[PDB]
Image 1 (cartoon, each protein chain N blue to C red):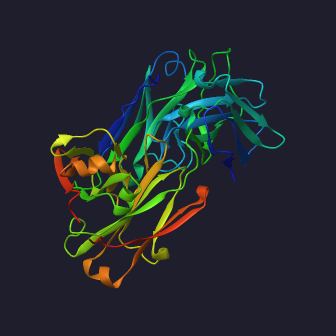
Image 2: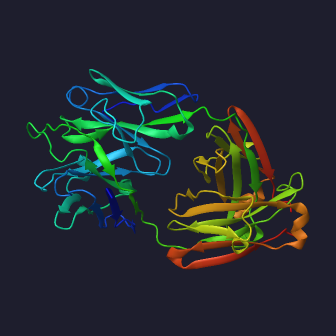
Image 3: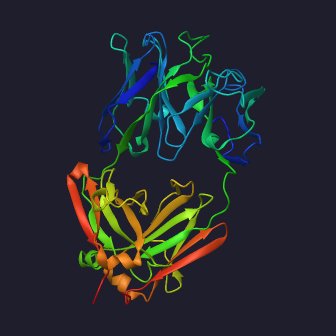
Length: 233
Length: 215
């Protein structure tokens, strides 16, 4: 029952705005102080801002002052974060969290007792980039002497230059699951993504079987099925 | 730069105990309560400890907290494989007028033997070369612990331009995978005799090679 569900994340260019939501339930949302904490991909937790039970007291990091505006709606049990003038360094997963205790203990503008963030949401992803939506080019990684060892050949597909994430990959419309190594994407200098997916199969099966990778990229409406086979002369 | 200083990584064996330090100043730890947070891979943070040494419901007594002036510690007795996580200490800083976190601490449990990487190097496809691009794909799998260095070469000389390498990522079998890409033009791909992907792991290297004349 006690939880926080977030939404409003997405992909936007530098300078644009985004509104995040955090719907609370299982407790009196109007009693507790609420936080926003963000985490850049593969980085530490950075506290963003905090708002009091009644919205009358707010604090935030210097990084986001004048750009981000924390607010809430107690009649609707929702926390908000109006992010304006977004930069590249704002790219992160944004969590909303609740104080452990409803009552705060201040002794001035600079002093509050830290009781800890007891409840956390699952997060919502914000990706700030100047790259435009693009579908992948799918190229075959053909099997060969250099791909084969001990009667087991490797073959795959190169999913190059797409934006944004994510891309799903399968083999033979899901019929081929054993030996599938789909690697996480690499983010290039151009702002475009690339990833590879490889299947280990018997060398004897190559001539009696056709292997097709099924690359799907929903943001660009790109669905490609690429036949992978040995190269000739 | 963080105000609270944690160690970037720690490690120990299942059954052993380990400590994670968190050092601050009078403006944060010295005059306030500290809380610790566990973040399991691919999940949101969870409150571990509050008010220096208190545990919420559902958190076992293996976890414990200590305080000694400006420093704070998180003790974990009887380690388990499930305790692999990033651990953060946090509090309010009265100078910055802001809630503050430490850099974090990677706890990796000694729960597996050392494993060498399997490397597979693919050359550019004819279809890619026909589109005036060229990408060598080096794929690295089944290595432990999760840390590798990738170096590329062309006729013996190193190449830093065009290299895009990814971080290690945990496979379903608890070993790690990674990949490195080398972007080229068709012209400079054909100009060299051979290219090589050299994957180093625990000081030991595995090399693979491709050439434009091959097929």
